[PDB]
Amino acid sequence: AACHNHAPXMPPXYWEGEC
Image 1 (cartoon, rainbow, N blue to C red):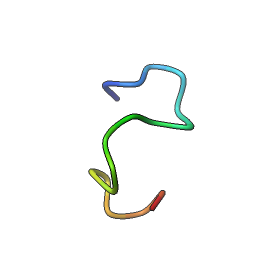
Image 2: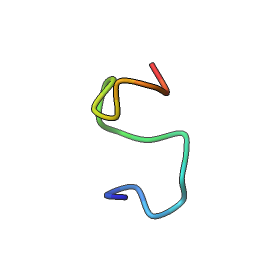
Image 3: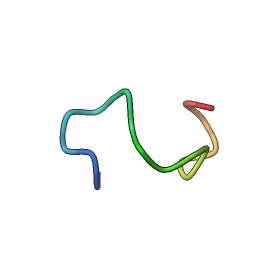
C-alpha cells in the first residue's frame, strides 16, 4: 500500500474500496 498506514489513504478511491 502506498499509504503504508493502511488508512486513511491519500489515493482517492485508488483501492476502489476505502472510498
